[PDB]
Structure formats: C-alpha cells, structure tokens
Image 1: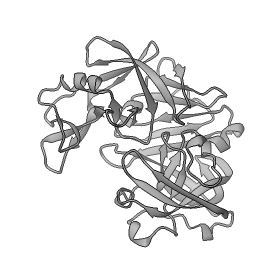
Image 2 (image 1 turned 180 degrees about the horizontal axis):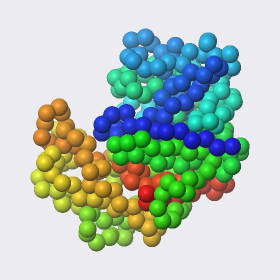
Image 3 (image 1 turned 180 degrees about the vertical axis):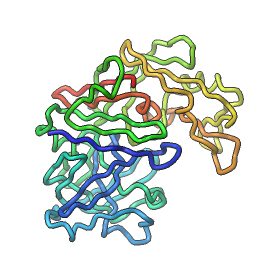
Image 4 (image 1 turned 135 degrees about the vertical axis):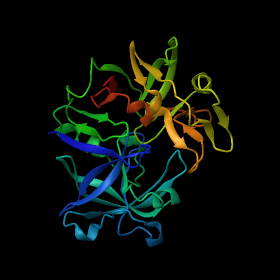
Length: 330
C-alpha cells in the first residue's frame, strides 16, 4: 500500500505545517502536525478541558464505532519548546492520504498547555520519530508509520515541505518526479529515538564550504534551524545589523536586509537554503526588527534540522531494518 497527503503551512511564515488525518468511523478529519521529532499521535478531543479548546477541531471517540478505550493507558508529553499535553488513549482506525491503519493508538488530550490552546490551526500531533519515544504508560504504543510499515510497498515515508506553499507527505513510495538530481543517503543513529544524522558541513552565501561534522536531528515538528553557536555566528556576521538579542531570545536582523543563503552538506552533496527561507518576519507587529530562521542550539543540547532546512529538500525517512535518511535538491 501507499498513502499521499498534502501538507499546508498554518500561516504566512510557515510556522508549522498541518496535514489532514481521518480518525474513526465515520471519519473525523483533524489537521495534525506531522512531527518527525516525537512519537505520539495525540488529538484535541471531547475530553479536553473546555477552557483549553479555542477553535480546534476535536475527536469525539464516543461517536466512533471503531474506537476502543485502551484500559488503564495514559500519556503525557513535554516538547523542547516548553509546551505539553496529557490524557488517555483509544485505539481507532486512522487514515492518511489513502493509507489506513486499524488499531492505531490515538492519544486523547484531557489537558493541553497554553501554546496549543492559542493555536487554533493545529488539532494535534502525529509523531514520526521512533516508537521508543512514545509516552503511553504502562504499555508503550507504536507510531502510525511503525504500524503501517509492513504493509507499505517500501518501508519509507517522505517529507516535501513547501516554502510559503503546500507540500506533500508520502508513505510507501518515492516520487521520482518530486526532486532534481539524485537522493543522497546518510547514516542514522536511533539511539536517542530521533532521525539523528551527521551533516558534513556548511557554507554561508557564496562563501567557501567548511567541512565539519554536525550531528543533529531531522525534525519536521521544529520550525527553525538550530545549529552550533560558531556556525550561527558565521551566518549572521554576513547580515549588516544582525545581532543576538537576549530579550527577544535569538538573532534578529533589520527587516530591510537581503539574507544570504545557507548550504548544508549531506555526504558530498549540498542542500541550499535560500536566504528568504531564513526570514521569520517582524519580532512584534509593526517592528522593523525581524526574527532569524537560523538560531543557536547552545543550551538545547542537540542540533535540529527543522523546517527551515527540510523545506529546501526532498527528504526520505527510510525505515528499513537499518534506517537511513535521504536528501535531494528540488
């Protein structure tokens, strides 16, 4: 089998991407944030504290004839951005772009943190990291990809995120019309439960490529590109007036600037992030100071190849017996 679904930016800045997901019988369609940095499929629901729901679409398991309460199961998650959610668990039928999993763990939120409430466009998350990170207790549950894998034509999914435009998540096949040149594959460590890999280096604008190992994760659920302080300083030094602001919480730059591109290495291959992808707009409405899309990972503890990086590429998440990651230009 295969599946194919369009993924759409939630706002004009590409702050995140939502993908429609069918849950239950009859189908209840929710718009979920596909997150290769986590491993829980959780949803706003009829069980969510009412004051914590503000415009989201909810899953109502009592209206699904295929929903079954997973007895005694609970979940609770906290994300790198400080947000969190928790609740109970059902199994139900879940379909993405034509691909159906029966008996998928659907984690129903009883509580969500303020940032989730405040974002009316995201109805929940669909985790696509390794199932070892799944938070369900006392019996850990599998991701949608893990459950579908054996049935897929090929044990892969691909992320093709758009810049200020829709893109595509495919399951089970590689669309050879969706990228240019070849796909370069690179080794993955699953030891931390992430799609963790090592970039071979970087360049800033038309500058010379610096060969240096950068270990990090391919994370569709993180907006920005988080890299070592040395790398980030080298980038922003090429932007007149750019500075790191402790009060704002990262590098900012004059909104009048033209940003240079940023290149990262995948083996001997090179992925070029155009400068415009690195502009996240005014720090507050009407400001002429703009927030940068490349930021320091110092104090995160890990480098994160988030949407800023991934949207410059066609990315293969290869879930073969030994997982690997593939990147192509597009």
